[PDB]
Image (cartoon, grey):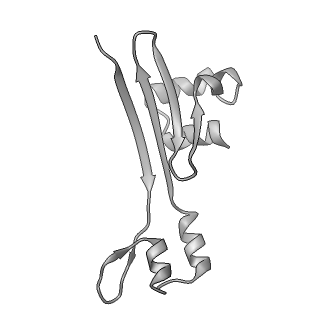
Amino acid sequence: GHHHHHHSHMRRSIVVIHPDTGRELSPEEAHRAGLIDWNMFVKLRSQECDWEEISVKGPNGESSVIHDRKSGKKFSIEEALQSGRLTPAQYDRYVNKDMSIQELAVLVSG
């Protein structure tokens, strides 16, 4: 038997189409191309999110960490169960695939 790494990754991105080159631009690039003003840029960003949950399944059992790829913050699940921000009632839903990566993010993140 060998270690398994379970990745549950979800992402929401937005692309801005150039009127002429029809090229896909990132809110960032659109802003530099003057296709959008600073506040629409912020607005657009606030709508993006990138979360990834990685369950290391080994010999001891399952270790699990969820990462906010947008902010760079990480959250131990065991550390969330211990500290109580996550109830073994909700963890069970995630484990049983009845809770999204985002619903779980919110629980442990804020």
Of 86 and 58, which appears nearest the observer? Answer: 58
Rendered residue at 50%/48% (across/down) = 69
Q: Please identify the quadrant where the N terminus is shown.
A: top left
* Above or below 42: residue 72: above
Residue 91's quadrant in the figure?
A: top right
Of 30 and 94, which appears nearest the observer? Answer: 30
* Above or below 67: residue 32: below
In percent of width and height, residue 89 lies at: 60, 23
Rendered residue at 50%/26% (across/down) = 64
* Above or below 46: residue 78: above
Rendered residue at 47%/36% (across/down) = 53
Judge left or right: residue 36 versus residue 85: left
Residue 25's quadrant in the figure?
A: bottom left
Judge left or right: residue 74 versus residue 100: right
In percent of width and height, residue 40 lies at: 57, 77
- Give the farthest residue toward the bottom: 20
Residue 109's quadrant in the figure?
A: top right
Judge left or right: residue 14 versus residue 83: left
